[PDB]
Length: 50
Length: 64
Image (tube, rainbow over the protein chains, first blue to last red):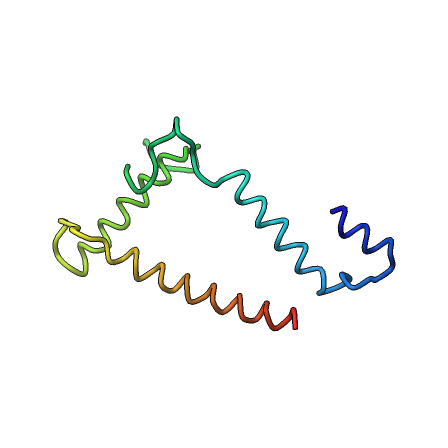
């Protein structure tokens, strides 16, 4: 978010409108890895073995 | 009764149902439940790979 704010304060306004699709998909992609993803060493069970 | 209506559910019940759905689906087309290998999975994943490749290219175009 800081990068986007830094560019908007700088006045490029390149991310306006459809240009915003790049920051949007990245933010969502990060969200999938941190909240879902897969279990650790103490969570050996998973769909392929169960 | 039981099982009817919109009651609560858990994540193990969601995968459990998807297992029964895959197993019953092949029983209609191959007439056996042995499920030595699971070809239904692979055929579905191949389409998802196809769609993803389409999205990557048009996003590449927008970047251009």
